[PDB]
Image (tube, coloured by chain):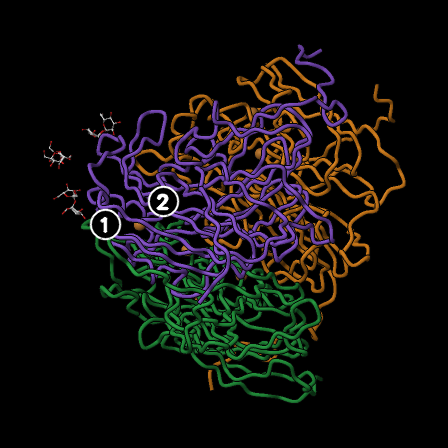
Chain colours: A purple, B green, C orange
């Protein structure tokens, strides 16, 4: 008989995050979320390569869910009849029943409601896990996201000082396994089912064909570049449900980084590159000091430049010549 | 002329650990251990794939040895005449002579006795290292284990509070390289010697055919599942002598984790997934809050589900509906 | 109008480091460095395999640059007309313009001068990054190095105690991708340009053919072994610009380790193996307790023993039988 107040959240597509408070005077609530599974063929690169995706809420990654320590998270998972497979959800933030997996298995046409208490602070992966060989396949097909469980007093630096972010972005990195035909071209399939045999043979060799942020090569570039201004403190949440990543902000730093992603631990300071362990999420905060283009990459540069894993930030403001200056422009050698 | 008291230890096969004290009032002793090398053909999967294993004491991993800071560890290594190759032992816990390697090289028919002082606390890898290209081959053939060097006052949380475990398990993860024939089937060999050429070609490509806990697919499942009860604090020691692993307790957490495995460092708290660097051991403690099945995996899920790297825990006790509850069971979508 | 004193540094080839102070009473200066790009065909292994290298100052890695927090680093980058490609430089230690990349693009025949303020302490990677698919190619061709930014008061253990090193070595690890012909032999090329197509196809498969310290198999062995004496505190700086490494000193430990490489964070103590994230540098200090040969390796032992990634230390001094002793030499089993 759990009679706490209820609060609905309207989830938003990554890399944006639904509005939330950092430090709050609210007590525990039941926070209500809904996720609807969609299986769909998507284009993942600039050459028109297709991929049989399975998603929460139609996006890779799934949306970031934000709650505070001690809240109860009540999720409605819906598997519409237009899908062909059973699905479930496992929250790394939750305790028991394989993270909820064992309580949320639903066939097409069904829905389920799980509630779990947010007893551990940090950013955590959630993903589908419908048993056996299906677990890796569903996850690398795009069925993963993250949840952020904040302390009620907001983030701190471990030395008693508040760390308040002006905005948060969620970057979900996805390793994809697209088989090639004899010619050397990527193959296309009519269904996830048909993709399965060839996709599993490739997965077991452990080398992805693509590594992408937000579902596609170039997803967070151009018009969809991340943005900030000089003086803004930005939190970047990064998740990888299956394989390690090494985030790096080219031209910046991680001023405060929780590489294991758990706010019970003090953050590390002044990082160049941090490490997100496969099956986890981490978070890094940086205060922009300079305008211009930044690239956020995994610093396996082959993955970043050749397999898809580069985002951009466009930052506005005034150039600081004390920090960096071109003393002499390119000129002929004397 | 080292005249301290002597204590013999009867080693036990993993994942169990020989009886020991955590905090102790004993002073330094000479703790005596014996390891006998066995080369043997073993079955590593459910389809009957065979593998030319080389082991300490007949198991993969080798047994966990437990001592306290300041003890002297005296190991008798025996290489019976039934073996075909020279072997040795290197302890990452020890100082000098390539970890003992340079002092323990023995041909079939010989034995040696090494003593080293346990000056550094934590869990450490030990492995065979008989020079040059043989070093990786012997290690990935199964010749590795771990030693745990406890503080005399037991483990602590870094904030002055004792951390006492009710039981400890040792999970050794092994990357195996089994070549395939033209047909696509795994190959079998009559000797380790004969396996060598094909095995080395495959090793150099860096992708394992199998990744297993305790020597075999499914070794820690079914009747040999790990066990606990709600309320029990369990320490899991995890080693990987050659390749990175990312342990994850599905349905739980790492309440206290030493991912680099060294007790001179405070543990991290509240992890979802931790990282064991190739050539190291780590340790994670969790107090079970819920009954039921848990899976302990490396959270490269392809490795976990498809290459062999999943263990189970069966936990007894009372379900806690506050922590997690199925609010509404699978029903048709309204 | 920046009128601070100027200091020139004569860079030295790795693994040596140019003379510097640890703790200093100097205030901020403009420290002046010059790097000259050389493209050249080099031999990378004992069987005579060749490789189209691109380097800073003719070495892989590029030289270590050492400054103190608050200094201004003024680098002249020179791209002589004997080179065939444009190049630039990105410092992970610097803030803005893609680490300087966006301000330092130079064609053969040109030079440029960049100045940046060293606001963050630690060891940082620098590398070429001339846009798009060229970025990984230039980096894995050898164009990377590191810079060390010291606190003005020198290193500390995080508990108020100074950590002073008696010598420092810089070990740069390079992943190389050398394609093979139909026969199975490594291919040779007349130019970097010609190597590009085949090299890029191989890079995208993510498995190196060689992994080497200081540019070549066996570079830091034999006459070029690293050296120390019992009682000496040695700092080893390790960088990897593209791919993870797991350094291990066989026979020793990391007494104090900054695995993420940033001196704003206290070091970890008593490590067996540490982890250098791709796109970063780390640093580990050890006081030698025993004489003899040590091997410093990445503890993927296949990489260490078979792909090139092993260095040696030769240490002089007196054997300590308390720490380790052969109690009984190899003898026949009774
Ligand atoms: O041209 C036939 C010849 O090509 C191979 C591939 O080398 O197979 C191709 O043709 C087969 C018959 O048309 C197809 O079944 C197959 O998918 C395709 O690779 C050989 O196996 C065959 O002898
Ligand atoms: O059928 C002969 C033909 O098959 C190949 C493989 O395509 O080799 C097979 O047969 C050889 C001769 O019997 C064996 O030595 C070899 O091990 C096996 O692969 C071809 O090389 C050969 O022309
Ligand atoms: O002997 C010709 C036969 O060999 C193949 C490889 O199996 O190609 C080799 O010879 C070609 C023609 O000389 C070369 O172009 C090629 O580089 C080499 O591999 C077959 O393709 C060909 O039928
Ligand atoms: Cu699913
Ligand atoms: Cu998971
Ligand atoms: Cu051996
Ligand atoms: Cu080792
Ligand atoms: Cu270049
Ligand atoms: Cu970089």
Q: Nearer the viewer, mark 1 or mark 2?
A: 1
Viewport quadrant of the N terminus of chain C: top right
Between the C-alphas of marks 1 and 2, the distance is 15 Å
* Image quadrant, ligand 5: bottom left
Q: Residue at x 53, y 38 (%)?
A: A169
Q: Residue at x 45, y 72 (%)?
A: B62
Q: The numbered mark 1 sits on a residue in which chain?
A: A
- In the rendering, which numbered label is found on residue A56? 2
Task: Identify the mark nearer the N-term, 1 or 2.
Answer: 2
Give the percent coordinates (x, y) of residue C124.
Answer: 66, 39
SS state under label 1: loop
The residue pinned by badge 1 equals A109
| Residue B37 location (% of width, % of height) | 43, 75
On the rendered structure, is A178 left or right of A226? left
- The one nearer the camera, A214 or B179, is A214
Residue at image position (74%, 18%) is: A327
Q: How many marks?
A: 2
Q: Is residue C41 left or right of residue B173?
A: right
């Amino acid at each position: 008989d759990l009679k706490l107040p209820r609060q609905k959240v309207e989830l938003v597509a990554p890399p944006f995050v639904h509005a939330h408070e950092q430090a709050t005077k609210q007590g525990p609530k039941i926070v209500e979320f809904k996720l609807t599974i969609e299986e769909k063929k998507v284009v993942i690169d600039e050459k028109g390569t297709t991929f049989q995706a399975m998603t929460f809420n139609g996006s890779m990654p799934g949306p970031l869910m934000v709650v505070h320590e001690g809240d109860y998270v009540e999720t409605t998972l819906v598997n519409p009849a237009t899908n062909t497979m059973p699905h479930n959800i496992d929250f790394h933030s939750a305790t028991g029943a394989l993270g909820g997996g064992a309580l949320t298995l639903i066939n097409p046409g069904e829905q389920v409601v799980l509630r779990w208490k947010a007893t551990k602070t940090g950013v955590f992966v959630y993903h589908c896990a419908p048993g056996g060989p299906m677990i890796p396949w569903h996850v690398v097909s795009g069925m993963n996201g993250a949840v952020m469980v904040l302390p009620r007093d907001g983030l701190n630096d471990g030395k008693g000082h508040a760390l308040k972010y002006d905005k948060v972005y969620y970057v979900g990195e996805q390793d994809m396994y697209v088989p090639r035909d004899e010619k050397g071209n990527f193959k296309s399939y009519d269904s996830p089912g048909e993709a399965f045999t060839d996709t599993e043979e490739m997965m077991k060799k452990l080398i992805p064909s693509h590594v992408v942020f937000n579902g596609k090569v170039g997803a967070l570039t151009g018009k969809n570049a991340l943005t900030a201004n000089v003086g803004e403190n930005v939190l970047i949440v990064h998740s990888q449900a299956n394989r390690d990543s090494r985030p790096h902000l080219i031209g910046g730093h991680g001023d405060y980084v929780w590489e294991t992603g758990k706010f019970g631990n003090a953050p590390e300071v002044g990082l160049e590159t941090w490490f997100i362990r496969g099956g986890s999420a981490g978070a890094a905060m940086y205060k922009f000091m300079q305008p211009g283009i930044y690239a956020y990459v995994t610093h396996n540069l082959i993955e970043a430049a050749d397999l898809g894993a580069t985002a951009h930030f466009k930052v506005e403001g005034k150039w600081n010549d004390d920090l960096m200056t071109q003393v002499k422009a390119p000129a002929e050698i004397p």
